[PDB]
Length: 111
Length: 239
Image (cartoon, rainbow over all chains, first blue to last red; front, side):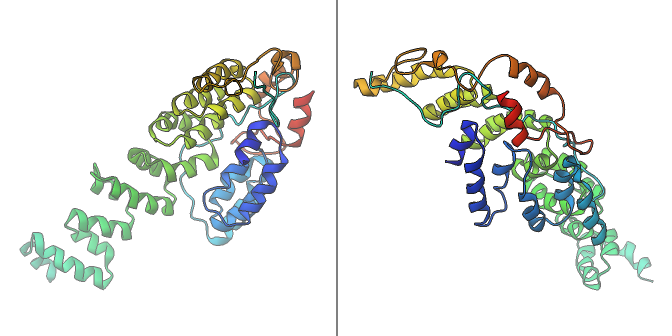
C-alpha cells in the first residue's frame, strides 16, 4: 500500500505508515521512507541501531549536518579510517509534474 | 632457547603449539608461527592484519571466508578494501547497506546488473527507481507480469506507457473475455488520457527539472552532493 502511495505522487500516507512500522521495530526497512523523500527522521532512530557515527555521517553530511555524526564519533574514540566509492550519485527522481496524472483513483469502463 | 628448537619443529607441531600460544594470548606471536590456512584464517580474524589477512586469503576460495571476513572488515572500518572483497564476494545485501548510506550510481549500475541477477522482482525495482529510471522499472515489470502495477507507475510518473501497456494488460484480460474484463479507452471515453490534462507530463516544469536533475538542491551539506525531495519540491513541481 505504501508502494501504491509512493507510486502516486503524494507524500503523507506513506509517512504515517512509516511511522507506524518504524514504530514496529526495523534493521533493514527505513530505506523505504528515505528515497522519495529527501529528509528523514529515521536517522534519529537509525543512529541508535548503528550508533557508530558512520551511518550517521554518510547520511548526515548533506543537510549540512555531517557534524553531529562526527561529534559522537570522536567521543567514542573514533574507528573509521577508510571508506568505499559511495558519494551520492544515483537519482531519486520521478513522479508526476502537471499534465498526465498520478492515480489516486483510477477510472476505467466495462466498455 | 626455544628458538633453537624452533628449527627443529615443523608442520603440525607448530600448529599444536600455536594453539598453546594462542592460549598464552600471544596472538601476534601465534601469528608468526601460524601454520594452516584455516588456522591462520581464524587467528587472522582475531588478529586483523588486514592486508595480511588478504594475502592469506590470497584468492580466498570461499565466499564464506569473504562473508565472515566482511563482517570483520567492516568492523575495522576498512571499507575501501571491504568493498573490494565484498564486491569480490559480490555479496550484494550488506554491501548495499554501505553503498546506499553514502549513496552511489556507479554501484547502482553494476548492481543493476546484479539487480537483474537476483530472482525476486522487488529489489530490482527500488534500484531502478533509485537510479531514477522509470524505464528500467517498467522493463523489469514486463518480464515479471506485474501488469496492473506497471500501469500505475506508467501513469504516475508518465512515460505514457499507460497507453501502451494498458492495451497489453487489457489484452490479457481480453483473453479472459467478458467486456468488463476487456475494459477500454486512452485519450477519450473511459479514460480521457491527454484530454483529462492533469499530473505526470509536460515541458516547462520538465525543463526546470531537466536542469534540476543536474544540480544539487541545496540547503547546507558536504562533497556528498544535495537533491532534497520534500515540501519545496512539491511546490516547484506544481508550478
